[PDB]
Length: 256
Ligand SMILES: [Ca+2]
Image (cartoon, rainbow, N blue to C red; front, side, top):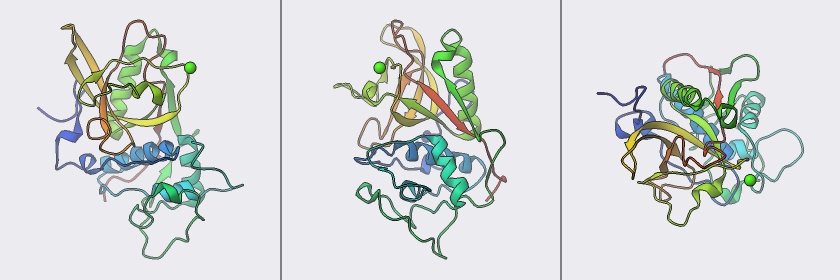
């Protein structure tokens, strides 16, 4: 055999599967990766609960927010802010109702229309923060446990949100098809998603494992917008390539 178990998980490889139907997006020249990764995680959770692969409007989330006006193009945020926005507005329009274009990040939050679909209908956030987060560096000496947490969440929810340092994937010979053997950094600045995993034999003939990572830099970047990366990385790295992982704890009735 199947598409997702404890050794191997790649839902992409089943053209007639909910999650595989969630096309890669491009955040453009705005620091909105937090929106794309967060909304994709909700979209996979919805898929897992029997809903259609309908995209959430990133633009609505970028433009609708309480308080003083912020520069939502130059300054990224977090997944905690994504939930905050949901709980505030109770409405997640479909992308078709309010499509994304990065030059429009900053526009007045639009009036919800009658014909708009609410992708957060009947949803709610579980108690007590509404998410669970893990730091790779806190598992430095039990990375097997970190790996198991992420696999379980990928299996059950379809993805996790992960934070990386963008520079670590900006190598001049970056290739989507190769499994990247990358270091991380002490900090992160870019949200992606882990969406699968598997085992491979590396260039030295040794058995290793990889994460399949979804990015928001369009489908030209990497391997159709994804890449594979060694779970443990080069021995000498002080920091794991995956800096942090975030999971949403949402309650959603199971079918529709
Ligand atoms: Ca640093």
